[PDB]
Amino acid sequence: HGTELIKRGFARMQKGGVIMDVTTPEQARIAEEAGAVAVMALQAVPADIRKAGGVARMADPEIVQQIIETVTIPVMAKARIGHFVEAEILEALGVDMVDESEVLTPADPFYHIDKTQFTVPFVCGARNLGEALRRINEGAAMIRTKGEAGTGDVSQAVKHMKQIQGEIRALAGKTKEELIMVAREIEAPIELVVETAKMQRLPVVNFAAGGVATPADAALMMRLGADGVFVGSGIFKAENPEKMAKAVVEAVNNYDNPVKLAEISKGVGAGMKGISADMIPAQEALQERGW
Amino acid sequence: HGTELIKRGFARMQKGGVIMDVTTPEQARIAEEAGAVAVMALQAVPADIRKAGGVARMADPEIVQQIIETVTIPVMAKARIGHFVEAEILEALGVDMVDESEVLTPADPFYHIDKTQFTVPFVCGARNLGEALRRINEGAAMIRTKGEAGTGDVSQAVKHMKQIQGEIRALAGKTKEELIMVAREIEAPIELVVETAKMQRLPVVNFAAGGVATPADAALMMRLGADGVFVGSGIFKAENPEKMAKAVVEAVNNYDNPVKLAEISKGVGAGMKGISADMIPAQEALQERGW
Amino acid sequence: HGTELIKRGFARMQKGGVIMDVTTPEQARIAEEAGAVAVMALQAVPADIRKAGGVARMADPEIVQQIIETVTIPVMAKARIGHFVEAEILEALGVDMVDESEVLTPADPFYHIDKTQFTVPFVCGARNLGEALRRINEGAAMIRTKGEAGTGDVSQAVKHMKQIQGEIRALAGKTKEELIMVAREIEAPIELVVETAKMQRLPVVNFAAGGVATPADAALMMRLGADGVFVGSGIFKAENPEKMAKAVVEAVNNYDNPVKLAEISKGVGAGMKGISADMIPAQEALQERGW
Amino acid sequence: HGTELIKRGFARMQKGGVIMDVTTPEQARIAEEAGAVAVMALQAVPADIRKAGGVARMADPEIVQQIIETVTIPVMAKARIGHFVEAEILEALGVDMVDESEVLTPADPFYHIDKTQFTVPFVCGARNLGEALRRINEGAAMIRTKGEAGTGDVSQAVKHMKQIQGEIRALAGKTKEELIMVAREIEAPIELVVETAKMQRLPVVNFAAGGVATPADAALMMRLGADGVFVGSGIFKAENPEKMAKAVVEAVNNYDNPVKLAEISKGVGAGMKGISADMIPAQEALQERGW
């Protein structure tokens, strides 16, 4: 199987980019022209998944094969939580990274995949520091904040990004006898809590996902310490997907220049009509999945 | 960056005036002719925001650019709570004051902007004396009562205005050992609670907002000690926006002359059909935002 | 009045020493010969105060005058909480430092003395970081952990010493927006929480008090980061006060040399028969005083 | 410092023996003649500690020096929980093993010693599998069940011995995905829970302590899987310490021969008058210490 370094060397190439979720070959072609670094083939954007309801599963193998033949950038895919056979079918198709999505219906209500047995690197969700460290223990090669997929509200993504980054800053200065106590409270391996405290960052690349809907929200996450952004319903549910796409990609490249950001936001168009994240009942919140 | 005095010298020029919220260049032209002191460009008046629902964001940069070119009085804008990048884009556009509105959807559920790092002065909401003093600590150059935006009921604005002004009157006569105890109960800096107690007023200009719907309500707030009034849905959701506008502006200039106030109120027209503030559930109350 | 620097320059001379509580001139003479740095005149050691009960007050002015004439090292005294007139009488007698003791019966159930109006430096108790910072705000020139006076159990002193020092280590690495949140939770001035976080120690000298009963416990507190130790009932309620005194003084000077510590502990004698700190009801715990 | 193997090679020499707690040189001489493998010097047997109350501490250094000069078998000692300076003084005296006893008054209510920094091997208590694995993580070179010291009731020791050994038997057959779930429930390192499951025993020597009072109880613990027995108040609080001593030592050597055990128990004498373990309130139970 692929060494952990090489899986933690496919996740580092994605730094400072944008990943756009697409459903058809034409949408995949659009994203590549805008300058994206990867695409995420799925049957329907997270906004539609809330609307349609029912049971969501892995995309049809026919679609993921067509997108791959259409773009040159790496292609990712989604699999249900704990469905180690779905992740086997995607890997055989040639995807470069499999995303254990909480958007799709969980298949195993207790366990996640055993990601160390596979070769393709994975990406997993995380709400706090405890969840980030457990996932890396299982072999996750990247982490992305859960947020609230399909709502267009960046309130939840910022909350989870300050929880992960807020805790990692407190670990500085603590003594060994205390870092052992923290590992108990957050229920994380003690080997990682010491590796994190020495580095002051998650030992794997960390992205932002859920609620990114405008060029301003994209550059906000990069100013909180993210290495990139996952943009889904925000672009292709907007007024003009083509214009919004180039704006978001350019926003991440100039997240620290206020003068330029004003230029980008002009003429982009109206964003997706979201849903207030505080309006969603807890039982309906996708973020609650991924124990 | 701009010195606190100059930011606390742009907020003082607005004393004894009216600020009217507008959405289109024509509405901006209307307000200026009525004699207003400033306009607040936004995508939709707070009355529509309740009706439309969804996620509300910063206005389109194209609109704020058009209003600025249309009026000579200063132009303000709104930004979401905690979205320090949106406040960066507005400042680059040339607005003279950015309003951290609780009407829009909060972007950060824990923190507000760090307003001391910017040059354009800010304005922030407040329900009591504790909230007013914390905001000024962060660099707010003006305070306005939250009220209940979009309801047309002046019950909530009066309540919050007697909470802020009622507390500042109790601080007179107290001894140092006691002013320290108050700062604990209201959770405010002790340096400000002593500056307030010596001045018997908020050290920054204070306006009234939310529920002002008639020339009588406008002059009521000025008789409770306000320095001005923020009028939003009240004017342009009324029967005749043009006539209501001149009446409200004239009401604030004669708030202490009963004979004249009768003359102003004649022929103005029917006010906006409001909503009883006591009918709104707490979870739906915009005033609860702005912790 | 004495400048805060000079009061924070009388507290620094006491670093790396032992302060022994004495009741009679002969006990005061004993402590000086053992090499102590100061004595604390009081009517009865904290062990007797629990036994006798009743109301405890400031020592008789006749006693404090006799001790001062007997020793050359500085003489301290105790005063009740909030009794600003008792602290006035001691200062006139010539004591060099007044100790706002929680052992004595509180006189004011809401407020402490206003220690900035006096010239003699003060010392005050503290259970956590919040209490340490409030006391320094009022003008305290030294801090000592409350512990559980008169029990001979070093369990409580260690607990409070890891609470104060444990919190100061977490403050390293935090950002300004977060140090403001901490100051709210611990209810401390924001100016101090930033001074502490930059220094990684309390800005004033910190001692250990309560439960020190053997040469081992004395060197334990110095190994947790204390600058000294307050030893009360431990020495003069032991089998041989003369031998225990020289041992404790020598323990603090060799707290980091295991070979020597064994030599000191040989032939010292039996320590005071203490009381298990977990056996004391909360209403009877002296540490609960000093809100 | 001593390698973990050598500390886990001083604990293995004690297999299949008896360790007798002694207070005076004569008692130490008695135990050696009976054929014991080690002695545990302390100020008073656990039976007296309950009766005397107060605060219990490390023995006088004079006593531990006298016992060592009297016997040829290794000499152990006790230290309070979390008192890393007391364990330093004993090591300098020449003891071969330091016992972090829960019988003595805890000195640190949150943490135990950091036993990896020392050279002398340690022994620590344990009520279940979770506690046994955490202690070994810190560097414990032996484990002994807590039981209920000083009661003479073998009900509690058997309970804890079936908890530790009962859990280790369930771990057989489980899959990796499940051994990770167990490590969460028992809050133990995942590296040890896999080492235990492969060996089907604690990776360090395990003894029995608390409630052993007769030659029958001694051989009962050895039939439940113990490697030895710690006998304290049982022998020297009995009718005839000399006869009981040889009986208990001989019981452990013939724990599996019913015919011989009858011969040993004849003429031994009356055992210590114990206290029913179910009569002791939880707050008074020594076993509750050692979190």
Image (cartoon, coloured by chain):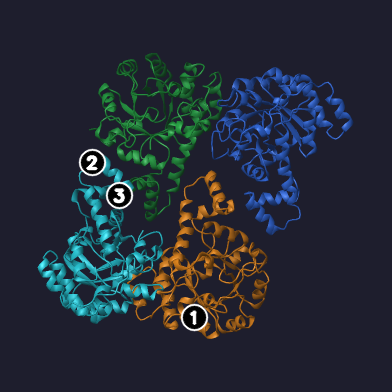
Chain colours: A green, B blue, C orange, D cyan
Front of the two marks 1 and 2: 2
Q: Which residue is mark 1?
A: C31
Reading the image, the residue beneath label 3 is D189
**Kind of residue sitting beneath label 1:** Ala
Kindly identify which residue carries mark 2. D175
> The disc labelled 3 sits on which kind of residue?
Pro
Residue in the picture at 71% in, 50% down:
B195
Quarter holding residue D204:
bottom left
Q: Position of residue C124 (x, y in %)?
A: 57, 66
Residue at 14% across / 71% down in the picture?
D250
Residue B44 horizontal side relative to residue D180, left or right: right
Q: CA distance from mark 1 to mark 2?
A: 67 Å
Identify the amino acid type marked 2. Answer: Thr
* Element on which disc 2 rests: loop
Q: Earlier in the sequence, mark 2 or mark 3?
A: 2
Q: Nearer the viewer, mark 1 or mark 3?
A: 3
